[PDB]
Image (cartoon, rainbow over all chains, first blue to last red; front, side):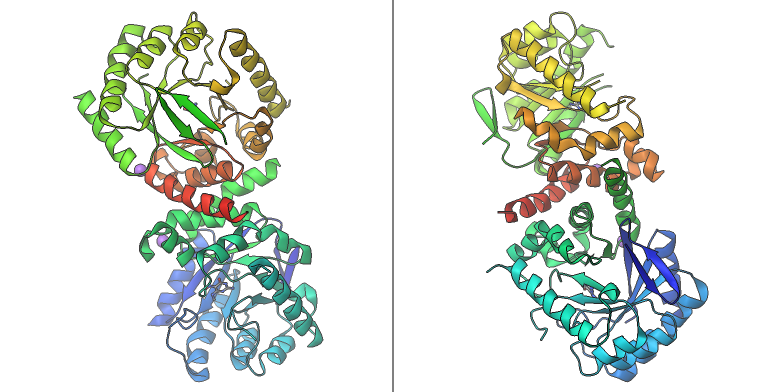
Length: 257
Length: 249
Ligand SMILES: CNc1nc(N)[nH]c(=O)c1N=O
Ligand SMILES: CNc1nc(N)[nH]c(=O)c1N=O
Ligand code: NA
Ligand code: NA
């Protein structure tokens, strides 16, 4: 399985680590953090602001363009690494593609006005995430959501092969819902689409272990390994070095299988 | 549910347990108890005492006082790393729960000593590595049964490392769940080993992420006991595994 963007491809025959680059001189700092993550083994750099954390300050289109576009450009000028952009705004989707973004990572699944059209115009891969807010058990709910959103994307001219699916760990989901989704993650392979997951330092680790946000590495690695053994294709994390190390062990095991 | 029984207590293996490594090889006693205490507080539910071939009198001197001290002070289960009948016998007398013999009771008198104790025994394996290990287990289970050790006293360990090469180690890890056909506890030890070091290219003190990854892969396949150096982090990883397996209804 492969993804295609900007005339290049990403080989999803093994898990990839996507490193989180939060950009909320900031530019020079962002490039150096990206370099560190690439050196540690990240093969996708995920560029975004603070505003995707629940509770965080909302920002203008103007501020998002000012913060994200130059960082995407600076990475494309320095590195061959794939670049994902965390945005829900159609103008950021449009402008990010123009400076070399490979993946549109919208936790709102292109629900904001004009986002669906902008994404379609770029022809880029798009990650669709389940969230409560976005326009029986929790697996079935998320599975139904994916069916619906895949349909919506396709109706707008976005080929299925451009889509990635993310069951959306966290974002207010309680402990049992999060672990149900992780336990059943492999069942989402029935769509034959890349699975992207993000559990790094989230509540499902913090609340389970009763530890603060800086004390969640071991739990985060365990989540990553559990997902990757179930064939998750991209793992979005804060701690790239350690996750990549864990993925080496996963890859050795799946190879032996 | 799978349980083990020893010294008038039981070990419930319906969830993974972390067994902390306690190397006594050379006061030494005071430091051994302190380390044991730290690992217990970090969530180890078995402490694995080993002091190593050294003479049997050396081994008795190193190991027995430590087992005895831990048994007197704590309620934690204790496993003893030994191949020698005298140490098996004396360990049992001072409160040990599991005989952990990497040589699977092959040394003279070991089998009889193990049977006489009535304690749980861990059997470790030392073209088709899965089939060879599986056949080994079949043979050793029969050997133990013949000596009067009930099958329900046995634990099986495929013996990661010990000169098995990288490919063989990962074949065994990938297929670990297939050893459940014996209906016996699976014990595994991958912590800080070369099967991690060779892949990560980091020294023994830098291998935690790989050690945790091995531990999680094994536990998601139903391994019952994970033998490790780094207890607190492994215990955390196991809670995440338990939350996942529990959610699988
Ligand atoms: C932009 N942030 C995220 N993106 C995706 N796709 N999935 C997450 O869990 C996530 N969590 O923060
Ligand atoms: C005493 N040492 C060990 N014991 C067991 N059962 N398994 C190991 O891998 C091991 N590795 O060192
Ligand atoms: Na870090
Ligand atoms: Na440690």
